[PDB]
Length: 132
Ligand SMILES: NCCCO[C@H]1O[C@H](CO)[C@@H](O)[C@H](O)[C@@H]1n1cc(-c2ccccc2)nn1
Ligand SMILES: [Ca+2]
Ligand SMILES: [Ca+2]
Ligand SMILES: [Ca+2]
Image 1 (tube, helix red, strand yellow):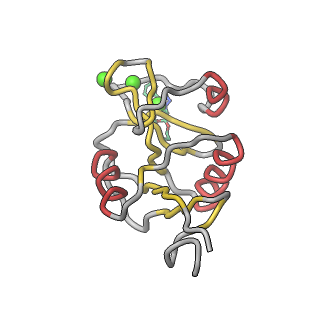
Image 2 (cartoon, helix red, strand yellow):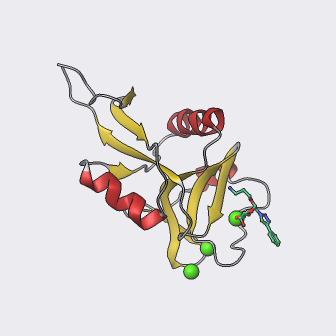
Image 3 (spheres, helix red, strand yellow):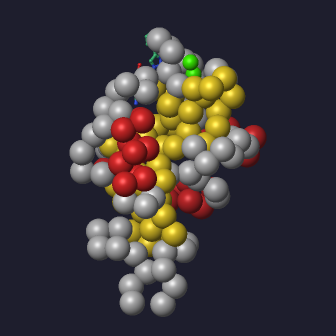
């Protein structure tokens, strides 16, 4: 019994997978659903640090499951949870700036950026671990 499928990274009771290909934000959501997972929704500061380190180290621009599609300037996670005030620190300086209408959040450098949802980027899926 192992807590995560092969190639998935265990962290604090959940399993994470960073793609080796790029898709747009909606196709990224689908990709995660297809493996019984979810375009990553971040619930803790420790989790955000963990994900940002890997995005920074890999130098990969990476979708997270966060958007202000439904109402501009109101960011919501894909599980419906609202973006809490304790998460505003992570936006890069000058972001979110919605330049050219940017409605999907990404790991970019040391923090978060809003970018065009049609852009192809890597993505991270999250599902819970088995117990063993
Ligand atoms: N992972 C992306 C790394 C590059 O980040 C820059 O370009 C992104 C793509 O556009 C923007 O979404 C970012 O906000 C950022 N940017 C552009 C701009 C800008 C301001 C005025 C005119 C043109 C661009 N101001 N700040
Ligand atoms: Ca919009
Ligand atoms: Ca926006
Ligand atoms: Ca931006």
